[PDB]
Each structure stands twice: as C-alpha cells, then as structure tokens.
Image: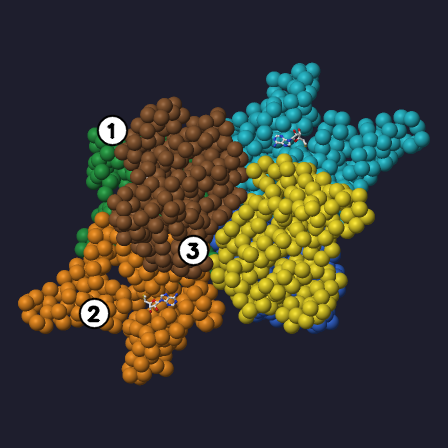
Chain colours: A cyan, B blue, C green, D orange, E yellow, F brown
Amino acid sequence: GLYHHHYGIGAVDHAALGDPGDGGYEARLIAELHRLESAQAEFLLDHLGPVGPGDTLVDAGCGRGGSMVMAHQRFGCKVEGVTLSAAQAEFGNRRARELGIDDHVRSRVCNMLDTPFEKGTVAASWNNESSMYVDLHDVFAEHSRFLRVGGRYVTVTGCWNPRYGQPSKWVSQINAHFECNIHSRREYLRAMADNRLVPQTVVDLTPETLPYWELRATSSLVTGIEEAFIESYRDGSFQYVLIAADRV
Amino acid sequence: GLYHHHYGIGAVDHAALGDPGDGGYEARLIAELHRLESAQAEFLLDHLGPVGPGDTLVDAGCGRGGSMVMAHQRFGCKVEGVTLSAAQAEFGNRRARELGIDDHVRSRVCNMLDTPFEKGTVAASWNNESSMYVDLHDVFAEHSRFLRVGGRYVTVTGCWNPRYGQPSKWVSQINAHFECNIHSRREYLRAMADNRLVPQTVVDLTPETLPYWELRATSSLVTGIEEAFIESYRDGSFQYVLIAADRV
Amino acid sequence: GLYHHHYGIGAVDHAALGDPGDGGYEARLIAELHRLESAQAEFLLDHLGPVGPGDTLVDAGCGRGGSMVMAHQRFGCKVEGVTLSAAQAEFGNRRARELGIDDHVRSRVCNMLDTPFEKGTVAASWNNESSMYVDLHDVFAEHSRFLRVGGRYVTVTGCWNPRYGQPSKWVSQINAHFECNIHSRREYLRAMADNRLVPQTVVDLTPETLPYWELRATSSLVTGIEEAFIESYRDGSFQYVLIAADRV
Amino acid sequence: GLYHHHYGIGAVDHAALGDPGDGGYEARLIAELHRLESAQAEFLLDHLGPVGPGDTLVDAGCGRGGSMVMAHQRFGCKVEGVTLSAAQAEFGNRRARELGIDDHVRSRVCNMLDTPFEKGTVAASWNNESSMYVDLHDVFAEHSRFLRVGGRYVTVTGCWNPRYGQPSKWVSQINAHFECNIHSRREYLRAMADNRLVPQTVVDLTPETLPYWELRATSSLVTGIEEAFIESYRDGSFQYVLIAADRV
Amino acid sequence: GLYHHHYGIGAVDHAALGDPGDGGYEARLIAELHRLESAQAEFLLDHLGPVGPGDTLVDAGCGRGGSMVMAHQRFGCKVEGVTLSAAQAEFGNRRARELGIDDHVRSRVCNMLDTPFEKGTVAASWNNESSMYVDLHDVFAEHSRFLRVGGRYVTVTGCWNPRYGQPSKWVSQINAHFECNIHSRREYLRAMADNRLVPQTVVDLTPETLPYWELRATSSLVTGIEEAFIESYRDGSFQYVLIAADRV
Amino acid sequence: GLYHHHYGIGAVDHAALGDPGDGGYEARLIAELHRLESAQAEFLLDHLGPVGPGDTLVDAGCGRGGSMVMAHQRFGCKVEGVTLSAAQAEFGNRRARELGIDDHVRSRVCNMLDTPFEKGTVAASWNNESSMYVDLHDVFAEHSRFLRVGGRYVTVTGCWNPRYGQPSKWVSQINAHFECNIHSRREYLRAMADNRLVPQTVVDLTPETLPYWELRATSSLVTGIEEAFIESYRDGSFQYVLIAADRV
C-alpha cells in the first residue's frame, strides 16, 4: 500500500470513483483504497477502550506508523511502534518529526517477540495485519507481559476458518505470496486463552472488507493475489476478523 | 417471566407504554418486557447459522420452550429441549401440541450435563441464560460431544468481568437470589477453547439489555434484584454477552 | 472480630460462659470467641513445620497481625505481613512496637498477588481466611515464587464442597456479605498442583468450627450471616479446611 | 503377610508380646502384626464415607480379600475385588464361600487399569498398598470412570517425599525388593487433580506405622527390607499416607 | 507417481540411467524413481518392529496400496488401508485380487480421523506422506485409540524446521501445490506426546531423499514444484523425517 | 571409571585385548573401556551441530571434564562445566591448566537446576549420563532458559522402556546402586516437549553399548551391577539412547 500496510473496510464510494475511462481513475482508486484502510484503522482504535493522554500504546508490526499517528491524534497518548524494517522505522519517525509529534510517536527496529517495554507498563497494544508473521503463543505472551493488568489488546487479521477443516489452497497461495504463515481462528482464540488475554469483542469483518478487495482486483497495481483473497473470503475458508481482548 | 425465562434487548417503546397513571400500565409493561425478550431470543437465533429443515437443534436449560418454538417456526427443523423442571417440560410440550408442532419440538426432564443425544448428531445448540447454573467445562464438553463437526453453539449469558478482578458484591447478590454460580468471561472463553468450541462472534450486549432492566425496576412485580443488575451492569463488574462458536 | 479476624475451633467452655442472665455474659462470650480463634491460629502454626529463629515467615492477608505476633512468640523468627488495609497495618505495627518485637514483626500495605519478597527467601507462609478474596492460581503462584524449595505453605479457609455440585445459596449469601469469592475444594487442590505446592496434610475442620459459630449465633453482635455458616456447614455444601503443603 | 498383604498402624501391645524367650513369642508376634494390619484396614474403611447395603465397592489390587471381607461385614454392601494373581482370587473367594458371603464378595483376575465395571456404578473404591505397582494417571482415570459422581476413593500407600528431592536409595531398595515403582506424593496429588479426584483428607501416617516395622525387624521372618523402611521413614525420604478423595 | 505416491531415499544408480540421449532415458528414469520409492517404503517397514502373521496393520492415507502390499509380502499379516479416493481404493484392491492376497490386504474409502477399527486391535500403523493433510493431534489420537498398548506407529513425512522460525516460502509453495498443510517438527513431536505416542527413533532423512528430488527435477514429467523441495531441503527450512513411536 | 564417567559404544577390539592369561590383560581391558567411552563422547559431539570458536557450550553434570576437554579440542569454543562434586571440579580444572586450555574450559560446583548462565547465551549443552539424577522437567527448563533460540541440546542416557510397562527390577537395582532415579523414555520426550526442546535425532544405542558392558562384566573391577545392565538391555526393559534436540 501507500501509507497503511493493512487492508480496509466499508462500502466503496463509486460516485467519487467516476468514469473508469478518465485518466485520473487509477489515481482516484488509490485515494479510495486509502480511505477504506484509514477507516479500518479507525475501527481498530474504537476497540482500545478509553486510553488517556498519559498512557503508552504499542503497535507490534507497525509498518509505516499510520496506525500510531492516528492513535496519537485521537488519544493524545504516547505510542511506541516496532518492526523489522529499518526503512519503515525511519519513515514513521520522519513523518512524526514533520507532524511535530515525534515527542510522542516513535518507531524502532525490534522483533515483536522480544520487546524492550517493561512488564505491565503498556495500556493497550495491537497487531494490525502482522500476527500472520509470528508464532501466536509467543507474540501474545509478549503482549501479555508488557501489558498492564486490565490493559486492552486488539488484533485485526486474516485467519483460516477451522470450521472447514485444513487450510484451503487459497490461504496457502497467500502465505506463499507474502512468505507468511496464516493461522486458524482456533489458534488465535487458543493462544489468547493460554496467555491471560480474554476476548471482549470478536467480529467477523469479511463482509466489510470484501468491497475493498473487489475494487482492488480491478486495478493496474494488481499483484495477482487479489483472486486468492476474494475466493477464499467467499467460500469461507479464509476470514477477516477483529478481536479485542482484556489482559486479565 | 411469563413465557421466556431469559432477559431482553433493545430500546423500550415508551410510546406504547403510555401513561403510568392508567390502570392498564402494569399490563402494558409486561407486554413490553415480553417484546424485548422475544427480540433477544430472535437475536440468538440469528447466530445459529443456516440450520435446515432436516437439522436437529438442542436447547440446554430450555425453560418453557419459548426459544425452541421460535427456532422451529423460523427454520422448520427438529428441536429437542432439556431441563430439570418437570412442570416446565410438560408446559413446553403442551404448548407444542396446541401449535400442532409437537412432532418437531419436545422438552424433557434431563440434566444438560448427561444428555441422551448421540455423538455428532446435533447441528446447533444453545444455552440462553442457563449456563450460570452448571460447571462450564462440563456443559461445553457435552455440547461438543453431541455437536456435529462444523456445528454451531451459542450462549447468551450474564458473566462477571475479570477486567475488574474478583466478582463484585452485585454478582454475588444475584447468585444468592437465583442460587446460581455466575462465571467470569475468562472462564467462558477458557472452557470453550478446552472443548473444541471456537468463538466466531463475541459481543457485549450490556448496553442493549440495560433499558430492559431499568423498565423492569419500575414495576410492581419487582423482586428487589433489579438493583444488583443495573448497578453491576453500570460499574462494569457484570456484563451481558452473546458468544457464537463453531465446533471444530 | 476484636483481634484475630479469622474463625475458631474447639469445644466451647460453657462453664466459663456462666449464666446468660448475667450482665457480663455478652462480655464472657467475646472472651470465649477469642479463645477459640487463638486456638485455631495456634493450630495453623502447628503445621508450619520446624521454623527456626533465622527464618522469614509471610502472612498473606494478615488482618491485625494476631497470627504474626503468635508465630514470632513461638518460633523467634522474622515475620512479614501483608494487607490492603492501611489502618490494619498501622495497628499490627503499633502492637509490635508495644510488645518490643517490631524488629521482627511488621505489616505493610501490599497486595498478596504482587509481593516485594525475593524469590526463594521465605521459609513458610500462610493464608488464614483470606484466600477467599483472590484468584487461587495467582496467589499460590506468588507464594511458590517467594517460597524456598522445601518451604511450607498453610491455608485455613472456607470452601464450597464440589461433592455436592455447584455452590449452594448459603455460600453465595456469605460471598455477598463479605464481597468475597469463596472457592471450591477442587479449585484449592487444583491450583496448588499447578503451582508446585504439594499437600502434606488436608483436614476437614468443619466439626471443630461448628461450636464456634453456634455460640456466635447466640449473641448481640450477630450480623445475620451466622445462619448461612451453620446451615451450609451442616448440609455439607460449605466446609472449613486446613491444607498444609510443601513447595516442591 | 498371612492374610492382609498391607502394613499396619498403631502402638504395639508389648504386654501381649510377653517374654521373647518363650517359644511362642514368634507366634505371638505374627498375631500382633495381624492386629496392626487389621487396624489400618479398619482405618481405611473409616474414610469410605457412609456406604449403604445397596452400594458396590471396588478394591483395586485386593490381595487375599481381607479388606473386602472387612468392608462387607461393616457395611453390608457388595464388594468386587481385582488382582493379577489367580491363586489370590481363588483364595479370597474360597474364604467368602466359607463365610457364607460369596453372594456379596468376589475377587477376580483382572488388571486394575482395564476393569469390567460400568461407568459411574461404583460408590467407593480403594488401593491399599497397590498403587505402587501401576502408572498413577491411568489407575486414577480408571477409578474415576467407574466411580459414581460424588463417589469416594481412598488410597493408603508408601510414597517418596519430594520435599527432599529425588528418591533416596532406601526407596529404590524397596522398589527393587518388590519390583514396584514407588511414586512421589507430588505424583499422587497431581494425578488425582488431573482425574477429577479431589482429596478430602490427606494424613501422614508414618508415625503410626513405624512401631509396626520396628516390631517386624525383630523377627525370624525378616526379609532384610525392613531396614530400608525404618530408615527412610525416619530420615523422611519415604512416607506412609492415606488420601481420601471425592470424584467430582 | 506411478505406484507409490510417496518419495524415495538412497543414492541414484547413474549407471543404470545411461545416456540422457537415449530415447529410453525418460523411461529408465521412471524406473529409478520407483526403485528409490520402494526403498523408502522398505525402510519404513524396518521400523514397524516384529509384526507377526496374526497382526493387523493399518495404513492411514494409503494411496494405491503399494506400502500395504509390501507389508504383507514381508510379514504375512493382515493389512487394512484407508483413503479418501474411491479410485485409489478400487485400484489397491484390484491389485490385491490379482496378487491373490485380497484375503489379507484391503483398501477402503474412509477418513483417517474417523476409522472403523476397534480400540486396541491394531499392532502397527503408519502415515507415509499423508499426515501433511490432517490436523496432527486428531490423527495421532485416532492411531492411539485403535493401536494396541505396546503397538508401533511410524510416519515418514516432510515437516518445516522450527529451528529456523516460521515456515519458509518454499514450504508454502508446496502447501499451495498439493493443497496440504505441512506441519512443524515441533507440532509432530508435541502431538505425539499428548497422544501417548513415544518416539523410539527420530531420523532426519533429508540427505537420503535429496538425490531423489535432484534426479526428478531433470525430467519431462517435472511439475515445477521440485524447485521448492530442493531449495527448502538445502537451506534447511523443510526436512524429510521418519519417526517410529511406541503406543505407551 | 578412570576419566570419563559415562559408558561406551562400539565393537570391542578383542585383538588388542590379547590373552586373558597375560598379567597385563586387566590393564589392556581398562584401556579398551576408555576407548569405547571416548568413542561415545565423540558420538555425542557429532550431534551438537556446527558450534563455532565463539560459542559457549555447557555440560550439565560434567564429571571430570572429559567431554568438555573433547568439545574444546574439536570446536575451539568456550566450555563451562557444572557438578556437585568439588573434587571433580578441581580435577577438571587442574587438567585444563595442564593442557593450557583453562582459558576456555572450566568446571564449577553448581547444581544443574540453578545455573549462573544468562538467558539465551549458550549455543549447545548436554547431559551425558547425568539426567538420571534430577527431575527432567526442571533440568530441561533450565537448559531451555540459558539456551539460545536455535541452540542444540543433547542427552545420552539410560531410560526404562515404557513399552514394557512399569520399571523392571533391573532398573530399580541400578537406581539403588547409584542412588539415582532412572526415567522412562516417555518422561524424556514429554519433558522436552513441555520445555521448547524439539528432538531432531532419537537413536536407540543399546546394541552399540552392549559389548561395552559384556566386556566389563568380565573384569576384576566389576561391582556386581553389570548384571542388571546386561539383562535389562537384553529383555528390553532398560535402554541406552541419544536425543539431540533444537531449542525452538
């Protein structure tokens, strides 16, 4: 993507898309994709509970910091980000300095499994499309450690549905495309329970993210993976969900 | 209650309530309470997935069969109910014979922990305000046993929120009132994971059930327990939730 | 209570109680209650094993320090107490200064779940009627941490008997009265096993504590809860037990 | 031993032992040993709760049926025994026919791990000095299966104390002597918790069984193993205990 | 493949391969591939222990029965096969009738997770390249059920190495190619331990199977997936192993 | 033994043993025993993976340092040893100073359960015939702690085979002889899985160690325990194995 690395949710604004014959259509599409992505990040924020200006938020696998900047403009709190990409950290910070908020928002190169945050000092943290890259038990044990008792964890992610048995080929094609390891909803809920994380909200967002991918499949920038997403989301083997949980 | 033994959800129809000075007000209130209760049972049904006419549904702790009759009029399937009360079974069946559907809907005196249903033959089952009377691990292990792989379990129940530590006095007052043992959301999610039940939807309904109890606290039939419900729901120590899960 | 916050054990000295017609009867009763309470605390001490003058003992949920002062006068060791009540800490310490033993015995405001004691430095610790206020797994994990390998843990507490299924209303009435969360004997034994605590002695003391509550139910100071205790102890749904365990 | 295969408890009757110079001393000793053994079996019975005439009791590893005959003469119930020795079964039954109670008491060759008793039909069962011959998790899972909910399990056995780390040589010498596999108190309590068996009474009987072994070490029939028992019981590495538990 | 559906092990016979210029080379290659495959199946048999003529062997995910026919010609026992493919069952049986051994060897359409074999009646069973298609805990729980105590389980399979963290893209490409779900060596060993299966032999066969795939990558029949196998086997993210275990 | 405290593997060199009539035979035997012992230690090293000069290796229960000196002469790395015997530590170090390598190899008196090594700093560690002296879960949890992610653990040890049920008398005789507590292969594999140790190689070495013990049973130095080893290794109740695992 251009800013947010995650996917979006919500009905597409076809009116603003205009004529696919215009030259500026492919541009008007990128703007739309962004709008839908911002909307889902805004939705993930709605689930962090009431974070105050004095709280410290953590974003595991923060990408370019889009979610961190949004968290700060909304809550006023301090936000620490973490990623494996140096280029991405530098980017997020550069953007913060420019916004005059690098005194609250910072990204750093660090593996989300071995973070520098002290036990029980984080008020809320999240994984926005990044838990598909790490063992679930270990990332949740880490969030649980640095999370304050009563803290809030949120994760928006794609997971294969165990209701239909083993992972469908679609899920595997996506895994191969991103060199990730998509987990099952069973594994998500299991790991959370074994790590003192208790779900407060579990919501399947597949219907809200479908328009996003259908619109994306009609572009130039298409990478060939949008087919896997659309089919798996339709036959139900793959699903987009949001899980907000309390660190009990 | 009068028919449904569970509680309701949704905004109160104050217009239909009219003048609390009318003699018929206390009557118009009972009708409203019923409407809200039917609405929540209708909501629990929305989470059973697509049950077909050939499926067999189970209601653990079925009360007077209100949820069973509703399930059948909606899906056309067979519905087996279970309770400890003989008077309640007789009632549910009597109502079925009268509706001319006792060839699909039946209630029987049987403990939900030791049911007669064969392994993997039930398509969907639920606990509507009755899981607060039994050990969670054992009732979920039982549902999991008679539930078909891919089947759907739903539970609407009051649970104390572990986010606020131990059970508040309010929760204990309710327990004493009904001689029940209200569980924690942690225990609900934990038991489900240890019994091959994977939550597909988790939604806090406390805001939707609050109007129900506030309206109830203003009646003659009041039992004195409505205070415990309203306060605990407000300070957040007690919460009303719906959990729909897949038997994986 | 007046000094010890716990309950007592042993046959009542009716001779010393004299005529319930005397004015001084209600006084002679308080003295008796105290005697029975001291006797049970003395009994809990009998289960700490051979603690030496150089050992450090811990009392989780120490109340007014009665058990701590008794532990020190008997063993000569150092005793650290912990409670949530500032007024109770101040009281215990004041009493220690007066006894000229505040150089061995001290109480402090601290939650028994997050104690300041170093790993493996405590020789023996106990919960005298206070484990009913906290999650069992967490308090036992904490005792296990600061407990020396080979150390001794003791707990005297009321627990609902799982032999009779769910908690009886009596247990719930008590919970509501003290805003506590009485656990099941199953939960006690389970938590101990998951936290390297191995029971050396398990003894039901309900028969020895019954006289205590029957005598108490005949006083002025009665709070109305003595009925719940007596009935539940009689029908067997509630039980008073002592569990001495080794930190293996 | 002569009848009971287990060990005994209680103070030795030195008066009845008389002069060790008599020829009949070695005989008077066997009679004493028996008395102490009967006394411990009587003690194990005290922990079966109130078994009625219509109950079915099970003895896993029943030896010659001494405990079964005693259970029946006391309760009037039906008692099924199980052992690997055909010669021992035949003996127990022969003794029953003679007592005119083989219509209640029966022994059979069957492994205690794979019993023929139906799920939930046994009221109480026990292992008197025989759990040291089988995996603990498997024998307790079996008792739990055929045990009625609310049933009572009792075991009197020698176990190495984990408070002193690994098994002492003494314990190993005994294991080699009987070709058994003495377990740790930790393993006993652990297995019970993982198999729905909740200890109601745990009592160290080592002091009550010591006189038994000291008297035994002074006989002709001595096998050389009494040294291992006496030393290990004294240094505390080995211990004799009774555990009565409820099948919850 | 042509007969065996699994992969092979052992040094390639380049001498028998002759000139890649011959027309008959592509034929001489298929014969070689077969030889290597037969050799690995022969190797899996070496790990079934001493199965006698009266034993019943099971092959979960049997393909065309090549391993079953080989097991019978070697041991003389009865061999039951299971697969999801009707065409494959018919094939295996047809081959048995022709060999005059269909009175010992039979294949049937049945899911390896829900088999018809009775508890404890199978002497040895195996998964030859088929465990990558099912949840590991469930297939091993099933083998454990129908496996006699002391029985032997063997599995030859490809598994991603957890020593290198998450699944490499190579593993994902293979998963997508076969629509399977390759597990981690950690998951293999974990599931076995949770299902009473104790490994007696664990051997990495990646070096012995490498020649097999290198020779295969030089053919006409190539499917494009041989690259994924060779690279992942070389960088160590994917590995071919054999695990022989006892049902304890 | 004389240097290595462990046992050996490999065919006996009868030619070098010469005439058992020579006076120097009993000497030529000790030399042979040593050769076989060095060979097995060399074999354990083959399973540490590619340890580099900058790695730190740990030997839990190091005896006289024979395995440590061998590890260093082969890899060039730093090797820390641990034992309970002061005399053994002094010996290992003395030998290191003499070899001019005490700047890489060191032994110290420390219990392998509570080591001073920092979390994740050790590249590979092992237990050569010493895990039979400690609880398995605790020693493996310790290795896992100080072991780097991706590190390698190896253990060569005698374990009773669970395939034959409970420990045979032979195993018990050995336990009594060394005052150790021989574990079951089940316990070895179980503990490893619960402590993030995943077996890469599991190999029964009983056939390779048998010649070692048969040759030993024909000497003067015989202690009487060689009978237990030979018989148990033959009837299969006891077994010598090597387990190499990765810290995942």
Residue located at (31% from left, 37% from top): F84
Q: Quarter of the image holding residue D199?
A: bottom left
Q: Nearer the viewer, residue B86 or A50?
A: A50
Q: Which residue is mark 1?
A: C103
Percent of width and height locating residue D189: 38, 54
Q: Which residue is mark 2?
A: D34
Q: Amino acid at mark 1?
A: Asp
Callout in the foreground (3, 2) = 3
Percent of width and height locating residue F11: 42, 48
Q: Nearer the viewer, residue D13 or E73?
A: E73
Residue A53 horizontal side relative to residue D24, left or right: right
E38 versus C85 height, above or below: below
Q: Amino acid at mark 2?
A: His
**Rendered-image quadrant of the C terminus of chain C:** top left
Q: Amino acid at mark 3?
A: Asn
Residue B246 horizontal side relative to residue C203, left or right: right
Mark linked to residue F161: 3
